[PDB]
Image 1 (cartoon, rainbow over the protein chains, first blue to last red):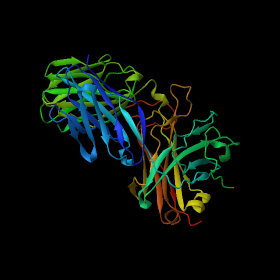
Image 2: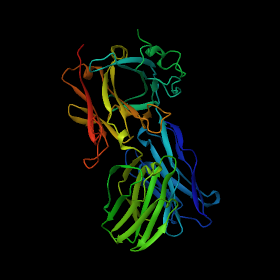
Image 3: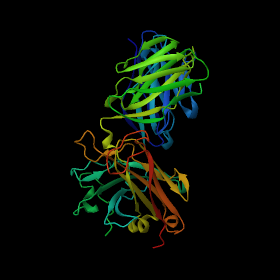
Image 4: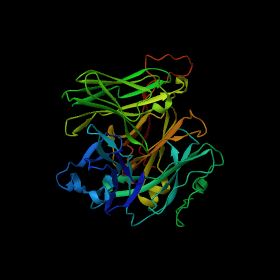
Length: 202
Length: 240
């Protein structure tokens, strides 16, 4: 009879904005409630828990959650979204006096604040001998998304954000490649809506 | 509660009995086996409050367990099938919901070991046009033609692992999406300053750890036996 519900498998937040991850439970009697984080590649870490006691609970790094019986809620918040907050988050509940049951998880995607975008498609060459190449779509802001290719011999990856700590510099990129003789980087992203000012060098 | 699990990574053929073992030092009464799958969270398989006390969780079908000792809780796949591919976590609890998780077992079940294949890995050097336009330089690593999807990719600069300036795709893509046993590919980017790329003394290596066959596995093909191994590709900096 008891369960826990997280809303949205994947959610976005702007870099710097309030973080809000929602959890609701279905137990008649208030349960104990838990929020775990799983940073990429790693196991589960407890952030905070409601174990009757205080209604407003505090975790590391600004995380908090308020138990609200009247709306059967235990939403996780943090005041400001940082790129390091990218992870999967799991709400969990006590059940049958003998276990913890886990929600399905929500992955938090943080959209970097790119104030000076410089969208571009570049061609890169194999370091070992090669008429072998890939195309790199890079430096676009977070209004651009990348579409899967229309052609079964062209491969296109999801966008990914890197953070060059050396220069305090973040950027988006997606990669495209093909074995085809007629594959040109000018055409690699034709199935995506790209910025009108994308740079296409010679 | 040093909670430990064995094995850490395993590939198995379908139709085999496979055992995962959980051990603890704190001797808590309560022990649990969960599986994690994308979009489903952690689902309970079985749990135990003492030796010879066993309770089904939500997904107990296809598994059995034994609580051989206060310190040990074993999970078996009775006859492995592909949808038992998952990350498996054991846990202990105190009597106040204080959970301790093991660090996980990544298990992949394949129908046919003949299809196992290590990746081919290549590094693609930065565009001149990027360097001129941005004064930054992005290297791309591509790992292709691997099966199953059971790899770890890392970058190494002058022999030291680097995390800054890196982004690796969160999941590999299927080379042939219509096939149940398609091979996979994966990309990663490493971005550095143009100055750093232009130093011919700097060495850049993409490393892919592949998990495959063990020494114990039969291999009947002429091609290389696809054992667990590292495959790398490299580039040096280029003044021109």
